[PDB]
Amino acid sequence: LSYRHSFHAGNHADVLKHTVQSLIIESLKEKDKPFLYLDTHAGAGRYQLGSETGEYLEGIARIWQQDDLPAELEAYINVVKHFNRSGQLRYYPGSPLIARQLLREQDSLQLTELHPSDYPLLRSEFQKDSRARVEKADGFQQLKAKLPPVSRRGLILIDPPYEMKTDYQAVVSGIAEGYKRFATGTYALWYPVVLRQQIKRMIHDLEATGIRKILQIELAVLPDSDRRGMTASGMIVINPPWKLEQQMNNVLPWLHSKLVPAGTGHATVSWIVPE
Ligand SMILES: *CCCN(CC[C@H](N)C(=O)O)C[C@H]1O[C@@H](n2cnc3c(N)ncnc32)[C@H](O)[C@@H]1O
Image 1 (spheres, rainbow, N blue to C red):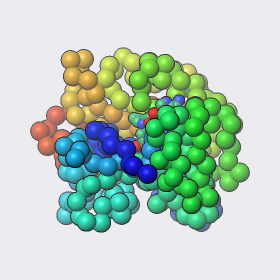
Image 2 (tube, rainbow, N blue to C red):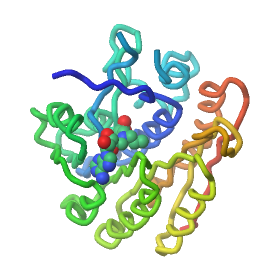
Image 3 (cartoon, rainbow, N blue to C red):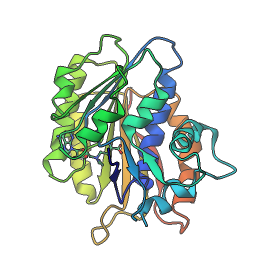
């Protein structure tokens, strides 16, 4: 009955990933046929901002009230505003609540979350929502057990914490088990850039699966470093919607200028593997 807190909720990485998620869902909704949203590392659902302040102040805060807000970011900010109708950031949606509000009545959610402290809160967020299934299990295995969805259209969101290095391996081995079973779905992998070499290994191991039509979006606050920590984050999208890349070239520059006012880092949208 008590919402979780999160120092990082709504930080620049969140803004990027929930932007890409929201754009992919809205592209899915263009056909009035149903689709699944599979979230492997779902977290609690929402996060009470502050204490009794937080990295949201340098993230969702810098963009959600901006008069010139790009039109592609509207569906995302409208979710944040639904969870903050006082006009003050006191809550930040998680990807499952992003999904809850954007998905239609006919659509389906599959959510997994192993930690005993969030699973209860998450389960309550869909307590009354039959579209979803919430389980306290390992989400990399839901790629083998939940796919393909009956609808045969969907978005898988793999957003691991990278607390153990083996998560840099797990996500690529998991995407291959997902892709064997459901090769037409859009997979979306978040990464933090702490040590680029780590990321470059991941990406090499991902093209080595042989999956094609792979895109890469990355928002860096600082040029790559080792003394700093998370100098960037990005999204690697497999089978993206065709407008995602022109949507992320139209948006990500603006995003970088608002989230990173001190003019450091970069904002890149590239193709890891062409079609
Ligand atoms: C950067 C990832 C932070 N978090 C999820 C954030 C949430 N999706 C959002 O979009 O706001 C990671 C959560 O994943 C849990 N977790 C860790 N390991 C697993 C596995 N193997 N399966 C499911 N869930 C996992 C953590 O407890 C975090 O709550």
